[PDB]
Image: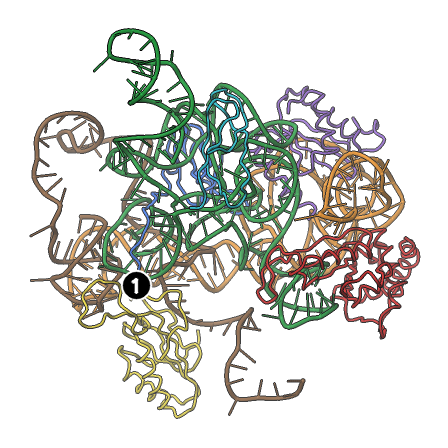
Chain colours: A red, B blue, C purple, D cyan, E yellow, F brown, G green, H orange
Amino acid sequence: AKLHDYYKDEVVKKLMTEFNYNSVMQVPRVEKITLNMGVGEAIADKKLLDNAAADLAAISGQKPLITKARKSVAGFKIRQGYPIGCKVTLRGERMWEFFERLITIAVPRIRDFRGLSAKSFDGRGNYSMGVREQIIFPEIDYDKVDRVRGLDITITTTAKSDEEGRALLAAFDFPFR
Amino acid sequence: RNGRDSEAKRLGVKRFGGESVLAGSIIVRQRGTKFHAGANVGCGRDHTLFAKADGKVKFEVKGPKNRKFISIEAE
Amino acid sequence: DKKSARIRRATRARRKLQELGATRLVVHRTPRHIYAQVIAPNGSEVLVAASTVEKAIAEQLKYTGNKDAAAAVGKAVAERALEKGIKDVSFDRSGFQYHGRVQALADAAREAGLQF
Amino acid sequence: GIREKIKLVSSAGTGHFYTTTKNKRTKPEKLELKKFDPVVRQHVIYKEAK
Amino acid sequence: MLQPKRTKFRKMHKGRNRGLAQGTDVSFGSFGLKAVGRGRLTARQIEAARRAMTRAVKRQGKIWIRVFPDKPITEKPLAVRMGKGKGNVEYWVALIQPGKVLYEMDGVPEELAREAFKLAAAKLPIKTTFVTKTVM
RNA sequence: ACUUACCAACCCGAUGCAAACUGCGAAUACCGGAGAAUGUUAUCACGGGAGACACACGGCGGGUGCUAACGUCCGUC
RNA sequence: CCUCCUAAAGAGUAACGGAGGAGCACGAAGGUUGGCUAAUCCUGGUCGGACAUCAGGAGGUUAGUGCAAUGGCAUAAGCCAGCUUGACUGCGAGCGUGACGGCGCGAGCAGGUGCGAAAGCAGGUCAUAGUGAUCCGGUGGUUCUGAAUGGAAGGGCCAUC
RNA sequence: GCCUGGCGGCCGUAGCGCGGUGGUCCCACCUGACCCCAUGCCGAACUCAGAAGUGAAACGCCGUAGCGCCGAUGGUAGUGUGGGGUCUCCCCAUGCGAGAGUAGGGAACUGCCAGGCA
């Protein structure tokens, strides 16, 4: 909520100035934020994926969608249709609320925080970063965990290149190494 | 090991371009829709094309994919 | 592909109307307007038309592009259809869902007296 | 092979039955369908039998 | 002895060897051996001719083989009757039509090329001729 | 992780091959309509009576055989 | 019995010729309404490895089809969901393919029904294998017959084993 | 006359890429989401109430032979009929005559209706 109109006020102006765009809508906009776990070992037991879904519900307000294995691979013992992960898509007001809850609260709580990567931009202006411990999030209580599992957060954008994607993310005070 | 075959199915175009047809006459028997159906031509469950009206058979090529269509022109 | 999806979604109904040889009342919709045409079986001549972008029905609307506008356009197209002598037609939603403004136009035409 | 023949008998008392097949091993619940009964000329529930 | 590494099928029909050769020009090297006649060229024959010409040019220049035997030829054993299924594959041949450039050669003088190709053609079952690269 | 006299998929250029390959594609044959001329109706149907169902070689297109056989098995004359 | 090739560009065409399958499956894997679009690879990303899920990009069917092969399929015939039983009953112009026994396709009419606002679609499934004449007999229905008469036995007709 | 939208004809000489260009109307994105309606999560899409902004992306138009596409003439292969040979394959007379390739073309053409601006 706050970061929405902060973007509209400050970030639009600054990006306009420092990339000489011609029209306002040329400025990049944060499209969506996708949180995901690949549950992995839960082919044997379904309960792990249910716990992961509960973790997603705790982190992001909306409930998660269970993803299927999409094919059969004999190496990892999977087949088409077996649940192998869980995902949440965040857009709009809830996207900005989660972006606050990440950037302000979860960012200062990485073990031996050596900054953060910057090459990870997909070459087209979309960011992705993995956290190694779901307990990093505040609502996940330290006592209500049966197994430790990290997750991946992918922040997409309407940017055309990694350079302006980096510019937009830096405008929100995102950490970098 | 190789002394086997199936009875031939007598598939093919049973009624050629321009010939007069009564309603219900099979035009072409086909595996798959090699000829599609156009005006006054019905497609059967095994993809047979038959005349839904008395007329004359006409072959054409239509559409982006250059597919062959069977139509019956009322004489 | 928000456009191409709509055309490939409407294509089956378009074609089926072509084999059936029906005079089709095609509806087009857009965030600001709604258009209606009645098109003969050959698919290349419009017998009657209607739209919110006119002046016969544009000043009697708070905002072109609402359910009231769709109802007005339906009534207008049905009235001119009956004036030109076309009664039995087939609705062609043109890939829009038969839910909102589209059905508003459709039921307006039905009430005005188009059989479909 | 495994799939065994059954008859679906009318619930209108006419003695009419359709005949079909069923895999007894999977889905053992009795089959029940609205079918046309020509003796009474109505659609009626037909129940698995035999 | 050349042979396909694998094939869709194991036994081909006899067919016919009619028509004129495609690939009738010296494309890679400077000199070539061209087929004036018509017939089969077996993998054994191809190996024999290749060995003869490679010995004629004592590890020098470069040699291309344009024909590859990809047709299985079956033969029934002795003391066996007709029918009882098609025979078993025994060797592979390349069908040669007139004009087919069989071998190609570069990096050698023309005299040595001619000598090597005479020694090679002494091993093949079809009449051949010497050809040289041409422009257009 | 250096590297490599062995090997090296992809892709790019050139080069061929295929009955069970085809982004092409004939000549013929076949189906249908119209028009003369010509032909002892030579076409169709129905009824009385059969015989015959070991074929042979030649030409062309092929399978098989060794593009072996006065070989064998098909198509067509 | 089904697919391809031999098979000579309509059909058809043989050999102890070359290659593969079938003797099922599914009350949903059928019907209808609405919606959707694959394989592969590239890049970035927690456990992650060449290959698990996510994000975007190139690509455009190199996927999928219940089971062989061929031919088809984007209006999709491929995938998903809601309601359903047309896997209906009597017929059927007219065709195709068989020496025949038969096999197959079929608009349309009557009855009643499902889905869809409606136009309409539906007489099983992308199509082509999944099969066995006749006789004898068993079961349900049907007062058709019923050997002096009334029944009944037995027989016929319809459905079915 | 110019521009846009809807529906057709034809189905790459019509496409894909590269460069430029347009917001009066139209179209596009766009603003919000109690309700109509919907997400196997998400107002992303479907859908509803609107019109602050921009033509950024999409879309239309214009230019460009980068790729696709089209493509002669002549020759060649093949082949019906008749004849011949050195008869596993060819040749002669006559009729039909490819495919590939070369030269070259190519930045589609057109019908009904509606709106804006002349």
Q: Is residue A99 left or right of residue E136?
A: right
Q: How many marks?
A: 1
For residue D44, side relative to residue B14 (left or right): right
Q: Position of residue G62 (x, y in %)?
A: 53, 59
User: SS of the residue at dot 1?
Assistant: loop
Q: Nearer the viewer, residue D47 or G32?
A: D47
**Where residue E135 sits in the image (x, y, percent)?**
44, 76
Give the residue at mark 1. Answer: E13
When asked about the image quadrant of residue E58, the answer is: bottom left
- Residue G41's quadrant in the figure? bottom right
**Residue nearer the viewer, C107 or G90:** G90
Residue B41 in view in this figure: no
Task: Give the residue at x 31% y 72%.
Answer: E96
Q: Residues within 10 Å of mark 1 (few under 14, many from 20)?
A: few
Q: Residue A10: percent from the left, percent from the top?
A: 92, 58
Point 68% across, 20% down: residue: C113
Residue C72 against residue G148 in the figure, above or below: below
* Residue at x-position 66% and y-position 32%: C26
User: In terms of depth relative to the viewer, which is nearer, G130 or G44?
Assistant: G130
Residue C90 visible in the snapshot:
yes
- A37 over H1 or under it: above or below: below
Question: In this picture, is C86 found above or below A5?
Answer: above
Q: Residue at x 78, y 64 (%)?
A: A127
**Which amino acid is tagged 1?**
His
In the rendered structure, the residue with mark 1 lies on which chain?
E
For the C terminus of chain A, which image quadrant?
bottom right
Left/right of residue G32 with respect to residue B18 in the rendered view: right
